[PDB]
Image (cartoon, rainbow, N blue to C red; front, side):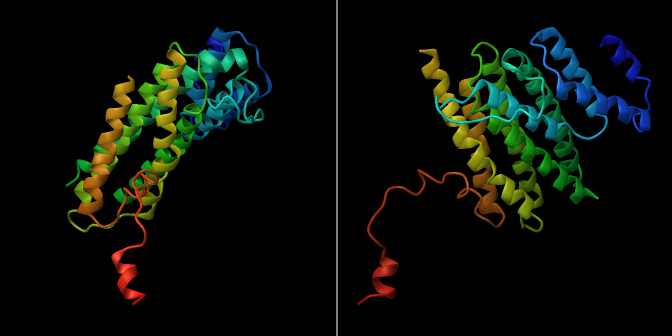
Length: 274
């Protein structure tokens, strides 16, 4: 495999040849298992190294994150899951330590890019198009994270590397929100794309994080870092909601924020009855 990588550096990334190499490395990841860790890691790197120069891995990560999630099981101790057909790599022995960290590492690279982009846009007092891209990217690997946060991971390094990645996505999200705090001062309206995948975090992410976070301390008997990144994320939605147009934060706390209840209201007492 070390030869195959050295040789595939010579392929023109645009070439019909390059495509073959990639699609074949997909086939090999697709149809074979081999619980030996050192290999599957190298195979995965090959695959990713090529994929990265074609289209962004976010789709692949989401796919693998569903195998890792399906094979190792869930936190609830009972939920039914699996999808094998994604990739034949990721066995029991494969995914738990190995594909897990390798997938996280890859996810962190995708975020450094989105970080880079968000950084680039703000640097400017064609651009709107980069914004829609930043979203789908984030949105996709939001589903990716939603998958591992439901997985029962080997506790040693896979718990903490997930927690690292988990707080990195919230930083990126935070700055993207902090980005629109710049753009909303001039005009102030929020693209559905942003509103929708802002509530994507309030449904598939934040609530799922919190239960993984408590699963970590019950299984036991980084963590405080995730918490911080989260609060700050909400903090700047708070600033963005009142400082642009829409209420973003009613997408996020859907449980506690409407709880304490009192019969009817003053509005209903007067307007309707007598």
